[PDB]
Amino acid sequence: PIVLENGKLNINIDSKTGCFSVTEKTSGHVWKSDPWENAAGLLTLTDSKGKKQTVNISKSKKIEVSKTAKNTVSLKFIDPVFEDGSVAKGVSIATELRLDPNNAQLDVEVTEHRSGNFTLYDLRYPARAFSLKTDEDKGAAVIPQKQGVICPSYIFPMNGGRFCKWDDATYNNKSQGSLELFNNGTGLTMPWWGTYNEKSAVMGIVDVSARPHMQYNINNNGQYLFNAKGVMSPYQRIVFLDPIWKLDQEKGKMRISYHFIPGGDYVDMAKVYQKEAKARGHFVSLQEKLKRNPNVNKLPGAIYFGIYGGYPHYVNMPGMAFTFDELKNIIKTIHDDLRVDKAFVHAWGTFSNFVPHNYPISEALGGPEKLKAAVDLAKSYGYLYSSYHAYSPMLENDPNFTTDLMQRDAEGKLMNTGSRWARVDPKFQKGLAQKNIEKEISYLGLEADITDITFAAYRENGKEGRIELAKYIDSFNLVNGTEHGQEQWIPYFDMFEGMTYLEDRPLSVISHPAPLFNLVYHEAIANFGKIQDPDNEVTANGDFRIKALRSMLFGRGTTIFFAPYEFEGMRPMIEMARDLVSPVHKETFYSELKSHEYLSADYKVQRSRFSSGTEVIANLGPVAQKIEGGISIPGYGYRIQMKDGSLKTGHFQVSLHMD
Amino acid sequence: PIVLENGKLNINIDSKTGCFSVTEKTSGHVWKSDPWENAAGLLTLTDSKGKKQTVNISKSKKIEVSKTAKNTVSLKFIDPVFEDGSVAKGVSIATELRLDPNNAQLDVEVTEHRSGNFTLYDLRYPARAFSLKTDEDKGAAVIPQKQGVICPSYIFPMNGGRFCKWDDATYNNKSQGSLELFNNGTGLTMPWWGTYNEKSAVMGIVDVSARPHMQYNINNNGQYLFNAKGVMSPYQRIVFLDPIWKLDQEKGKMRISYHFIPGGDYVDMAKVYQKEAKARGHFVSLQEKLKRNPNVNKLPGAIYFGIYGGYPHYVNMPGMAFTFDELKNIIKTIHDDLRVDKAFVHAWGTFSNFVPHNYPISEALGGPEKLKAAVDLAKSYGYLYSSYHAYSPMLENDPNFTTDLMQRDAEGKLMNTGSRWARVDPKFQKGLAQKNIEKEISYLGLEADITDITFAAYRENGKEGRIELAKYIDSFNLVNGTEHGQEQWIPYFDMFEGMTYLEDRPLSVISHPAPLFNLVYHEAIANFGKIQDPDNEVTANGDFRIKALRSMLFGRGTTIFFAPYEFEGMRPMIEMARDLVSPVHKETFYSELKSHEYLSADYKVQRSRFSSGTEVIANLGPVAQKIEGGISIPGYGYRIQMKDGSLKTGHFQVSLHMD
Ligand SMILES: [Cl-]
Ligand SMILES: [Cl-]
């Protein structure tokens, strides 16, 4: 082998294949190259007939590996070979491995690619690296899918229904696939991922300029590679996560930085990234935000209430719209009867035109003075208030619909024809906001704003116009929120509505929620439940029992999101959130989520520690379980140590009243 | 126009296009032909270049429409034209429309197709027929997707989060697609579907010999057709369901029979089908089953308990496997402490080999005598008992794994390499069951059996071997169940585990559960909740509150499916099922589900009436709502009128106990 080495790592590079292993010297843990095919990389490209095929670059006609500097090895893979034995002449991939001279940190970069008369598409590089061996390694893959998850590398006790679905998925196509960076769908919210066992951890951080996808393989033995051939896989069940470099699209630097952490797990990974997040400029603390705007302290302990009037979808829809008097009375009841001390009231349906014309205040719902009376009541209670706003939609049912503000592609065709909520080109969105937002703020005396859609993702197309809008909104210095968010938007907002979990998502049945994003960013952005999956709805992500406990563990706020006709049914949930979640949310709001742990074999009992001095232990399953010191946590129960040393213990119960 | 007419229907057939309208003469409602393109049919076929294209068959070069009998119109569509104006010379499609002389029934059949030098694939015929106009018709599409759903043709009040998902799905690809018949995944469990408004209903029943797919379009304006062109749809939002004849594979008769019901809805449609089910031989009543086997009377009021010991997935898995003494104690606790009077105990993990070798009784778990003691205990209480059995798997982790009993295709390649649970060719399965099942029956004195996997679907490949196993099992005259089921298997079993709902399914955000299967088959086959989504798990399909109420409305039994370590956490739910669900299940078990109705604008308050003289009203949402007479049904509440005149009223409560 060729060798790169420092005080912490030894990298062994195979001259013949370009594959590498990483020995973490302190533990003797060796991270292995591809256990299945000894493939350094997997490259998808067209053949001479123009059919896409995926090849092992380690089978190329020529492979050149050399040390080109003390801590750099240069590799070159020349003329890959197709399945049928023909050669992709003139195709080459060049890469570098660069060891930090001091730290346990390896940079891996794809530095050039040549396509000849072929077309190159995906490159998995390194391929099937940093794997865990299922049922040998006791650890997990770590994936910042929205708030984040882990995927254990072994089978463990769990509810029998869940166990069937989990195990089964590890033998079919549910456990393999890919995810993308910085969307509000199924994708990742931070540019890293990793694997750990009981000895060591590795993560990879993707260069800021690049947008690889991430391939996963969760305990799968690769049977998916053999089904079309009708044979059984000869490979072993493993866990891996690989970068997919999109060679046909990517113009950035195709670099991933691997960090090796002895005895580390997902918390340690998160903290490594937190330092990078700060270097990248995303980290603007809620303490800095509170210094700029004292009204940010209306957020700790506040329930986020969304009163959904059928808008933006419809204007004054019968059986859904609220009047402004009705809004006022919901506000009053929240404060006077349900004793809610702090709240963020978000009223969906206050305008008589469709977004993106967020005006005038609707005469049919009572007019301006009647809305002002609602808002003033809220402000009298120290609640925050915002209308629903959006500057990105262009809706088919809007009488003012036009394609004039939609974007066109290089061929002159309309973009986002199938995505109605994100049709207005961002380059127009600041101008739309400017039409009325300052009038609303002046007329209502607003202290807060929430703006939908535009900041839910961080794609390249249109980003300049989105930044312009973000800066415009931020210039008002209101306590402000937006739908979902991404790390890149943290500087401009105080809270994100969402950054939790989709209901139906890849990896659902073979992962556990982990507060990855909040382990990084809790001190910098507040988050609340998503409006589609609020704390009052029973979904794949739980009922109120589960959601309330998870809120405290993860450091998010309560979301009660309702049509007006449901309000009386919200009362119990509001009370329970007020009693249990709100004081914990208050105490921990500005703090760091220092650590999170799973404390039971089924992963349902967890412990979170916040730099406020607050410790939350909760049991998200139905059966009491013991942890350390033989302490028992009831099903759907909690034990919380507050800053002041007091202890709160308790549990939820579901009962049946029979008359 | 050519007309077919009787006293109930007028069929108006356009002689230039082949499109037809149907006037239902009692209500006067007119079902229109394709509102979008005036297409009589949509045919997918390869072009001169071999690229598949879809074409409107009404644009064919020659269309021949003639009245060939009093009540038959014959159509021929000759030389379809491609996008580019080129012709598919030698291609033709012939159809017939046959009006029943007396009844409001129309048979539609594709009687011939010729391909010439082209290859034909899908044919939608009739295309976009029997549609509902969104927000003008107040009705629904009716789809027997597993237990069944309806898809309303208008927007209505509901929870705000649900509303956003619902409306949004009508404008993207979530509201269009296709489903297949007789699978245990996303598909249909009865060969019919339909549409209704406030005046009239139509359904179509597919010929017994055919396997069309079904296309859906739920309030979608056809934007999916235009996204690639980057233009806005010019079509209106409508609801339709079309048959998709797979011309490349279908050997049966491509006939659908349309039945027209003035004032009808999904209940009337289910009852039309019920007549056809009986004609097809699927309907063997529970009453007949009870006459054959008096032990069937151990099912009414019984909780289905699955004790999941990590088998079949693993043998004797630490932390999941139960011993036979442990199983005995669980059974004892359920009866003596939790006062469950009737139950079906299903123990997953009683053998020391992997399925499909369902023997011997495991020595490691205690041996035959200790299993007998647990079974005898169960029998002394009157409970039904089965071990887990399966004759279809061939598992990678089984030391005895071989490919010898796997099916191979015409190229000699293994089939089902991707489906571990369904690998043994059905032709072998009877033999595998024969190896030990009679030894088990005799040793344990079994009164019952549940067999997993084999009867979850009704596919053509392997059907004969499945039938042979069903008949073999049924020859024992045991109270018996199977996973999921299908209508074709009703004659052989007393119960099905499942026939409810997938958690993640197409149409989930744009449909309501409706008890379609049970509206047809409740008197013939009992069902219970699916082990993956049991009444103790909180999922997309609800928590215990919601599941228990739906169980009573739809006429299914309770499923408690748990790993042994969870048992103590099951107690409250077992109690509540005992007190609430079990007596209603007991009373209604053999009865007809006569009617189901949605009584609230949000579809959450419902009413079912059983021929036992039992009426169940329940509210599956959080807020109290009023029905007729101003009677209020509490959130998560019920009002049940029993045959004995008694009225049961009550509701679930979730409380927080702070110590
Ligand atoms: Cl969360
Ligand atoms: Cl159900």
Image: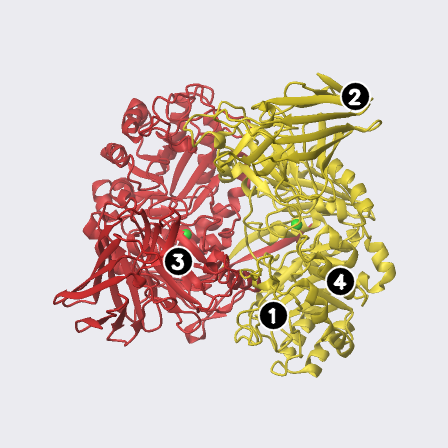
Chain colours: A yellow, B red
Residue B22 vs B474, above or below: the answer is: below
SS at mark 3 in the image: loop
Q: Nearer the viewer, mark 1 or mark 4?
A: 1
Can you identify the residue that label 4 sits on?
A468
* Residue B382 visible in the shown view: yes
User: Is residue A30 in view?
Assistant: no
Q: Mark 2 to mark 1: distance in Å?
A: 59 Å
Q: Is residue B480 above or below residue B121?
A: above
Give the SS element for disc 1. Answer: loop
Callout 4: chain: A
Q: CA distance from mark 2 to mark 3?
A: 64 Å
The residue that mark 2 highlights is: A5
Residue type highlighted by circle 2: Glu
Protein chain holding label 2: A
x then y, percent, for residue B511: 44, 59
Provide the residue designation for mark 1: A404
Percent position of residue A628, x then y: 71, 33
Residue B620 vs B540, above or below: the answer is below
Distance CA(mark 4)–CA(mark 2): 46 Å
Q: Are marks 2 and 3 in contact (CB under 8 Å)?
A: no
Please state which of residues B554 and A34 is positioned toward the viewer in this rendering: A34
**Residue type of the residue flagged with mark 1:** Asp
Q: Is residue A472 left or right of residue A355?
A: right
Q: Count neighbours of disc 3 (C-alpha within 10 A) and say few if under 14, some if 14 to 19, many if 20 or more.
A: few
Callout 4: few (<14), some (14-19), or many (20+) C-alpha neighbours within 10 Å? some
Residue that appears at 40% across and 48% down: B51
Q: Is residue B422 above or below residue A468?
A: above
Q: Quadrant of the N terminus of chain A?
A: top right
Residues at marks 1 and 3 on the same chain: no
Q: For residue B84, which numbered disc appears in the image? A: 3
